[PDB]
Length: 151
Image (cartoon, rainbow, N blue to C red):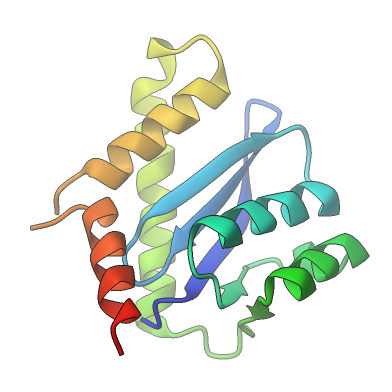
């Protein structure tokens, strides 16, 4: 997949909101637990992600998520463009559903090893990214980005 493409969605659990970002080419995930879905939270997460990885385009399965002035400002500042659903590449959509499915499963498995849901979500990200499938998603993302540096 292009190395600059990410998917970003929110999922719901225990009355809280989990923002889940997946780097399409590797399956690596980043997530945060946010009070409720807001354009301000989506924008803040996008700016954080773009300062950490070379984010070129972001796709989502809820296009309305990216309407607000504040999200448009964050994409403008960071130089991100939206990847328009339209025929969401079949291999790509399959990566995204699969990583999202895997994360929700892991959260459930570690949930009682943490008091708060946000702690279990980050234990689930950690497990997910370090799981060898072979290399892990964490290994794959650094390989892909590092290889992309050198034209």
